[PDB]
Image (cartoon, rainbow over all chains, first blue to last red; front, side, top):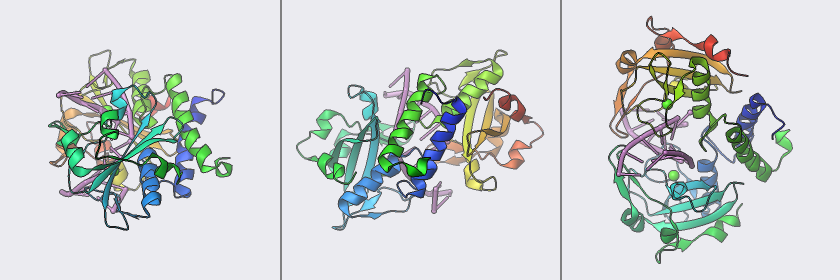
Length: 156
Length: 158
DNA sequence: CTGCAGCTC
DNA sequence: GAGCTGCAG
Ligand SMILES: [Ca+2]
Ligand SMILES: [Ca+2]
């Protein structure tokens, strides 16, 4: 992409978003990671996608589980800051599904974390009125956490 | 043509374009490019100093000392009220906001310098996020105390 | 920990 | 109004 002008680079950024939405891979104007991670969890659970602005959770599974999906793109597996999950303002869900992409947007690691374990790992931020969880290796490897890496790779 | 690419190739191109924009200094973060790119245009237009990326309240200090809070949206529908909603404001310690409205090809469509006091008048509080919401509606853009910066920003995009 | 733009109805 | 994901020091 080094041969493209900056104007073309910005246009490719928008056009790729537009084509992804046309294919139903994403459904919003956000950067694709959030919607794409939800799509994969939906495929893996055969679940029901919630309304985009619904509070608390994103996907309801066939067995009735309410899943809060949280994704990050990892460019440096040793950068703790890239493990910071998007803020949590409501605990009315059954489990979080953490989806860690590599910088080619391939699934690197995924984990199903019970809500109670998420709460135990959370720190409150008064600035944003919400809770921060870090998807550090210790949480991903927690004895009550399920490794979902292969389950999400099989739906990529 | 992107319609000929596999979904895997599309996603990789999404990352690759972000990486190339950061390598060139057009952006300086892994966010979607709009936020950093709007700050870059305002910096080019004011010859100002970029604040630290995690700095509270403002983004750019002008040579004359104005602390500018840059707020951008990419407009796909010029008549859509929701697309004027600016990112939340949790601190009023800035002198003026610079609103940058892009079109869906990432060209500058409209830009405006809004005094902080006018931003405060238009804001509604959201207890859910502990912040203030301002909409870049035409009435705000056309306010008598708002400066049109569209041509300034257009002269520095490439 | 402190913050920012994951890092629409 | 109610909400979401406009990632960094
Ligand atoms: Ca989510
Ligand atoms: Ca800003």
